[PDB]
Image: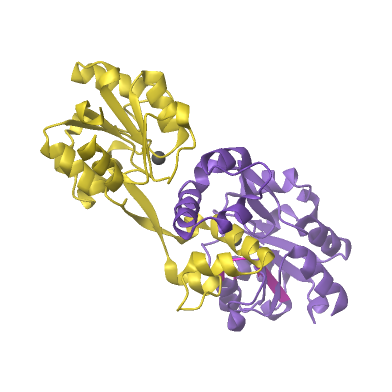
Chain colours: A yellow, B purple
Amino acid sequence: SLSEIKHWVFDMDGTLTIAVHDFAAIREALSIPAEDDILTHLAALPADESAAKHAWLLEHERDLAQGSRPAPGAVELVRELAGRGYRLGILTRNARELAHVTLEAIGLADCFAEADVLGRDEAPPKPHPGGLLKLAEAWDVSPSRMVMVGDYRFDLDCGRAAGTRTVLVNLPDNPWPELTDWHARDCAQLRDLLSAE
Amino acid sequence: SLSEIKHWVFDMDGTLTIAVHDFAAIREALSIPAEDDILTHLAALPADESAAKHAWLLEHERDLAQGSRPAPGAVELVRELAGRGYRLGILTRNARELAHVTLEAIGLADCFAEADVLGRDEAPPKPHPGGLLKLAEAWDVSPSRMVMVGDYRFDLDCGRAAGTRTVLVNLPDNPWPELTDWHARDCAQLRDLLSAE
Ligand SMILES: [Mg+2]
Ligand SMILES: [Mg+2]
């Protein structure tokens, strides 16, 4: 049962936080009417114009980015787990300092012990198991009793390599069934699963 | 007339080259059937699943990127202009060395004099006019007789600031009419415009 796992490890980008983008710049560049939602409008254009505009959006993802915000239900999930006294960690490609700043920004800095936030300098890149093995050792716990929560195949591969359980969030379905122990559309639904199962 | 302009300056990313992405990874992550085109499939999903999957694609643009390839008609346009004996330049945020490598990769290194490829270290970031002013001076030409070709508002703003003519490519329409002297869906159509007008 998911509620039996008391040691949780989170990816950051795409899991606890998501990139936000300049909506007004997007609307101007792609000629979206104010009364239309961006994606709904693009989906309704002729296929060739839709493809061209989507390709442009993707090409300029970084130009249009404006930092990040908490992913849906992420703050809620982490606070729920922290409230249970569970042990929480982070395994991110970000530098530890930046991860720290982000955690403070989204109001979750107090939910993770500083030593349990592993960044660029503390662990090899996913899907290398190193970071999870480090946490498992620091926590004196079997990996089979930890869960790795992520949104990308490398997060799941990392969990499988280290031997932890794995959770996919922030996709609506189950694209890697064999790599994925639990899946939820987002952290809010994951919190619901935790509560029910 | 466009054919009267004999001094042309190109942006790189999004104009002469475009990022390519890992199609197989995308298809696996978003559960796209082999017989479906990715975008057409997403456009046909329920709106909520479509939005979630598009947001994921955008969030992982850099994870899914696999270098770049020539933009449609770009090699053809540059060779056509070089063949006319026109003077050609580049104004890119990329380091000059990388711009050089890219130009070699796509077979256009011989179309630009090395001194006329301005990168990170040779010119301030768009939309600062500096890079175009530098080329105009090096070429002993009035900016009104140069054209800046780009795919982003900053390219057009840069041209307007320096006083060059401006061209938008790689969007299908005309989102910044006042900033844009000519627009074309891509470099191939731009070559056609050049030929006809
Ligand atoms: Mg991630
Ligand atoms: Mg560009």
Q: Is residue A38 above or below residue A125?
A: below
x and y percent of residue B152 in the render?
58, 67
Residue bounds of the magenta highlight: B146-155
B151 relative to B76 in the view: left or right: left
Viewer-proximal residue among A70 and B183: A70
Q: Is residue B17 above or below residue A178?
A: below
- Residue displayed at 14% across by 41% down: A110
| Residue placed furthest toward the front | A196
Which of the 4 image quadrants contains residue A99?
top left
x and y percent of residue B79 in the render?
83, 58
B171 relative to B113 in the view: left or right: left
Which of the 4 image quadrants contains residue A130?
top left
- Residue displayed at 20% across by 39% down: A195
Residue B122 appearing in the image? no
Viewer-proximal residue among B194 and B130: B194
x and y percent of residue A174 in the render?
45, 38
Ligand 1 image position (quadrant): top left
